[PDB]
Image (cartoon, rainbow, N blue to C red):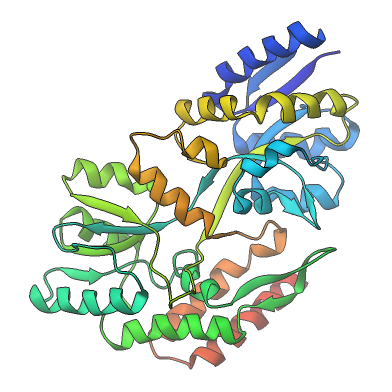
Length: 373
């Protein structure tokens, strides 16, 4: 009997050597194969129901809810080392009160700012708004104090979710996709704060990803909301940038960005799940392995004590801190219609074509209608 793993390209070498350690101690070889995320899911969905497919796979946390309900991935037994993982990363791989994977990477946006215009990170969103107005005034509109992809629900979620909005209500039986909180009082308050930034001129209805991104590269945007994926282009453009978590919406009320997480999962139909689980919890999950995984592919780490090891990367520290206060993108298939419905609602709001209340309630109605079909 041998163990089979489907992993990413930059994980093969690390997992092959680790498997050699596992073979020496237990006498079970480990076969490691690179498979891309898209093909992992399509292969797993038809191999796993028969007991085939890899014993261990990597994948996105978004898959967990459906793989868990269909009994294809195995609940991770609690082990002590779990205390060293970010709560957001563990929640992202949890469903119905059970952990279903061991995460290794996170991704979330943060505040990125040009230090030629911002001397200290604003402590609150009210301070950010005042600073943005002052910057707009000082440079006569040539420099935008604050700009981001405002009508995109992924980028505006820190405000809508931070004030109390939620996508699906969490219950002990799993996410209740019949209970959608995108129009409750918190969501309305978050959307009203976005609308206030529009009304005061700090944001405009024409703000989108492209205009934000190009303006920051050219040195004409003081503060933006973006992720680690854009940092290289800003460095190459010669921007003296800094990264920090999005300022508190109010004192004591943090911004709550969406977080994407990648992790390892166990084939629940495999005859080798016990040996596969041992290797996952005792070998893959260890701090030393996760640090090597980070070095070979620097993504925001899922372990707190791995971040402590880094080192020379202040950007990763800021983005990881942003992810820690964030919330996972809901890991169920019913999340799919939410993006476009909320993006339409945001556009309607910022263009003054409906009240915040009416636009959000319409968005929830359309989400439910599409979930039903």
